[PDB]
Length: 249
Ligand SMILES: CC(C)n1nc(C#Cc2cccc3cc(-c4cccc(C(F)(F)F)c4)ncc23)c2c(N)ncnc21
Image: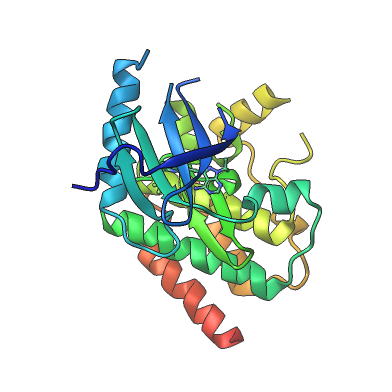
């Protein structure tokens, strides 16, 4: 139904790469194309599921899914985002954000994640790398991909993936936004895994910036609760951020 006939898509410069590679493309304007290539049965399965999940999504902070192509090769085309991911801006570009932009980023990410969970969709790998800033003001959530242990919840470390795992990952992003640096900065990787997995280790909330609102730190701590059931739902935290963002205005 959303299939793009062959010949319409023009594939351009290569961006990323084993299962598939993504290119910048032109289809009624700037678009991104993720192409396949032997296609593994799991790879074909993931291709089917990604199209199935993406078509059910129509939200501004969720990466716009424009279509899929089959004739030349299996491919999925999405909107082209100009800018860099949240991970690059915070930890690689060494660019300090105004607090209003930070809460706006957390507010925007909260909207998309709440939209996903409202659609019974779980974003199993949520992290600063998977948050893209279109232009520099609008955030787009997508699967721009072991490498993401820091965002993994205690239960997923021990053994699983659920809404509670997603909201915990949202907490680390809150820690990244407010502190400006990766969690567990003091620590090595095996030491972090065992300590966090056993519950001995938790991010250092004192490192947060002074301008951080009191409600945000409390909200951040609530998301990082070791008990899965203790973590708040995305409707609650979206309302809290938006209410706080409204007050700041
Ligand atoms: C960083 C740089 C190399 N890169 N990679 C871009 C891309 C892309 C995608 C292409 C085709 C299908 C996709 C599906 C998903 C996906 C899958 C499952 C769940 C979710 C969700 F749950 F998280 F939503 C999202 N994510 C991304 C793409 C990209 C871009 N589109 N624009 C600028 N730079 C870009």
